Length: 110
RNA sequence: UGCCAUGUACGUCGCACUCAAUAGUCAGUUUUCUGUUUUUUUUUUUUUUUUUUUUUU
Image (cartoon, rainbow, N blue to C red; front, side, top):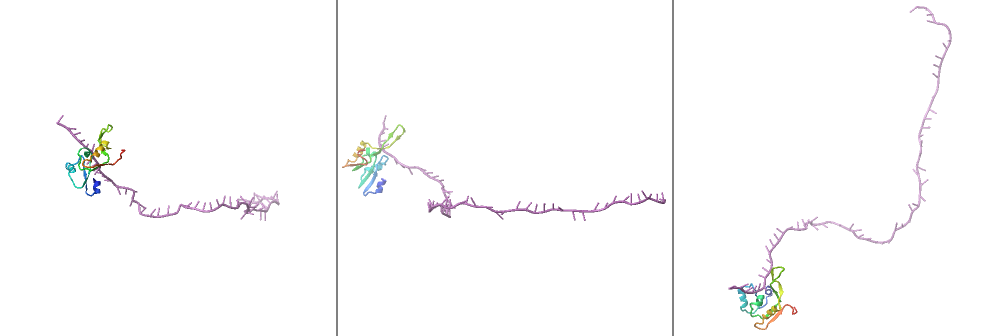
């Protein structure tokens, strides 16, 4: 968000979404606008909220995932590449209203 | 308190100071660094920093 607001794209506003987000802000994601909104979201939008009015989707293929190992006896949440099913879900999150394009910031072999 | 017999033997002398000067043996390639003063103090205690994610009579 700071990088995009430093970029200052014309007729474009920057909109976040995550789990700890305010209820009012989560409704402001849902409300209308004028122009283009670049939404930066997480597994919340991957799974639950179904943010509307999205044309294209960027998948870096990256998510923290909870984990619990026997050596450390402690819950961790490492940064791991998302699955094929997670990639397919993030891909399908954009073809709701019209034609969708999923730009994945990694390789097809990967 | 009177007397004491006669002749009877002599000379001259020495001492010192000393002694010097002597044989043969030629030569050693070119070039080089090395070098000097001056400000001096070198050294002084620090700190809290980010967030997958989702459900429970």
